Amino acid sequence: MSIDEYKSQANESMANAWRIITLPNWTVEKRGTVRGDVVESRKVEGFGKVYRFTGVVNCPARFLYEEFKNNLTKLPEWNPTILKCEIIKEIGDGVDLSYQVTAGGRGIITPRDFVILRRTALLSREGRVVDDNPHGYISSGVSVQVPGYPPLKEMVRGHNKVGCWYLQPRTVQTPGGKIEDQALFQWLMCCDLGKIPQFVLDVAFATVMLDYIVHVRKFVAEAKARAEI
């Protein structure tokens, strides 16, 4: 693919993720331990069943955005569900190609690898790209083919149809009266996985998404402890 085909597909994917993740009327799949954590699903025409995690993380949304944007290769260090992450190429406008290997879930979601086209951007409330004072920070992802990264015989090549991390900044008052920045964290995931029935898939997807947030929160709490935030 040309730079332009990839940049096009990254833009289209980012607009699709933003449109989806802010659609109304979702169904609850699974609640987490932490108050407000939820995995929801919806039918989306041309995607099928999409899943969305929502919950609050105790850090500035910019901090996490910058970690995801600038330190994607370090995700394995703090997230055990991510085995490997490598930047293939960075093609401008916060667009890049990456190779990622994920761990298995309950034995439904097995280890998989992915070739991911991402755009990371700051968005207005209307989903336009801004340079500053964002309404939200987004990192969108879609699977693509990159010559040199064929499917391996020893691992299932996953296909991410649409997905994103979407962070919205929040400033709250603590119980002690401190004012501190927090982030609403949303994650949209839509895969083609077989003939495994949908009800089996729904439990396995929601469980993966709830396991992942544990490691984000641990990463945050370690950052807080070390006065990085």
Image (cartoon, helix red, strand yellow):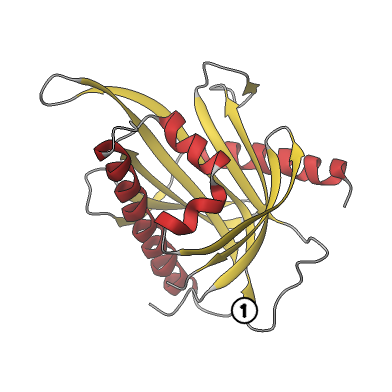
Q: Nearer the viewer, residue 24 or 213?
A: 213
Where does residue 186 sit, x and y in percent of width and height?
Answer: 44, 42
The residue positioned 62% from the left and 18% from the top of the image is 131
The amino acid sitting under disc 1 is Met
Residue extending furthest bottom? 153
In this rendering, the answer to whether 195 lies above or below 171 is: below
110 sits left or right of 120 in the view:
left
Displayed quadrant of residue 226: top left
Q: Is residue 227 left or right of residue 122?
A: left
Residue 63 % position (x, y)? 43, 33
- Asked which secondary structure carries label 1, the reply is loop
Q: Position of residue 208 (x, y in %)?
A: 41, 63
Residue 46 visible in the shown view: no
Left or right of residue 207, residue 179 in this image: left
Q: Residues within 10 Å of mark 1 (few under 14, many from 20)?
A: few
Q: Residue at x 29, y 36 (%)?
A: 58
Where is mark 1, residue-wise? 155
The quadrant in which the C terminus is found is: top left
- Decide: is 218 above or below 131: below
Q: Is residue 75 above or below residue 90?
A: below
Specify whether 9 is left or right of 155. right
Q: Residue 138: x and y, percent? A: 55, 36
